[PDB]
Image (cartoon, rainbow, N blue to C red; front, side):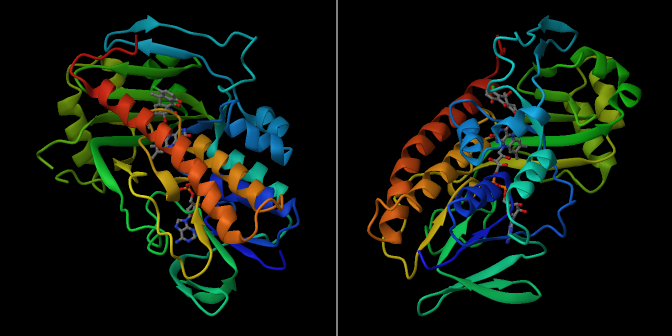
Length: 366
Ligand SMILES: Cc1cc2nc3c(=O)[nH]c(=O)nc-3n(C[C@H](O)[C@H](O)[C@H](O)COP(=O)(O)OP(=O)(O)OC[C@H]3O[C@@H](n4cnc5c(N)ncnc54)[C@H](O)[C@@H]3O)c2cc1C
Ligand SMILES: CN(C)[C@@H]1C(O)=C(C(N)=O)C(=O)[C@@]2(O)C(O)=C3C(=O)c4c(O)ccc(Cl)c4[C@@](C)(O)[C@H]3C[C@@H]12
């Protein structure tokens, strides 16, 4: 390689891709939407499985650092009334597939690992266009740049996939509402104490509640349900409008959980989406281009596949792009994509499948 790569998106999947390339010498860049490095990343915690997510960290020398920040966490399962199954973390296993890390923390660990100015902040890729030998990358109100390989690694809603595949995202039919509570122990004591330093999942009448009670000192919860045919007709801008819907749905549940709803300051309602690995991707492409993470195989969050498969993506493509066991870039990508279409479709089938089971009328996590 006498060339350069451009990864669109500073996600955990993108930044990883960046490290694994950079430590092999390959000249690389990460164009990130976010306005600066201390931008707050909304969402839960992530857990890197020992088979996969962890392996990539290993190969970047960051596995250790990952544990250092990660927190092993037990899981309580609950009725609407009260407790059902507790499960602590047995010390034989607290260093594996469990350790829940804060999304920002992971990025901090990743940004450290990269040379300075590897990530160009406030760069919102609006358009991608292939020239003679280089792609031309267009960013909203910033100068364009060019590169010899673009790796799309920029979210399940990537607006810029066209050169790789005509496939488009699809809503699965469920919906998720997600929120944070700061100082959970004061603002939802009832709920905090039901968690008891442990994650919490409870299900009742095709309504699922999940919670982590300790995400860097804030509780993050999720509510889930098949999308109402009524929908759409809840305003995620008016908190009163969201609260009123959740209370109608959650009327049955204990006083403790209703506190949680009534306390949340603001909600983030996004539908469950899939970007299916259905057709093979375009086999004639103007220049070399590929996709990793959710830009590749966006799938329902109901299985902890997601970041893990996506990190595997980096591990594989990065190896391919460095070992010198391929004759052209085309071939190295075209090979990574074969493998991903395999464990990828697996991960998706699994997630879809878990999705179906949970919202089935009468479900218990036991
Ligand atoms: C509610 C919820 C819960 C989830 N829970 C889990 C889980 O528990 N375990 C798991 O493995 N997965 C989970 N997922 C999926 C998980 O978040 C993703 O797999 C992973 O975070 C996505 O990694 P990524 O870097 O490929 O995507 P992203 O993290 O979305 O990274 C893309 C990056 O590109 C940036 N970007 C977007 N557009 C542009 C652009 N135009 N130009 C430049 N940059 C851009 C974004 O800002 C972002 O920084 C969950 C998803 C949701 C919605
Ligand atoms: C966003 N939503 C889907 C869930 C959610 O709201 C969570 C949260 N911390 O509040 C999660 O734990 C989740 O985001 C989350 O992390 C889950 C998770 O890790 C997981 C894995 O890895 C394997 C099997 C299962 Cl059944 C799960 C499971 C159900 O615990 C999911 C739940 C989701």
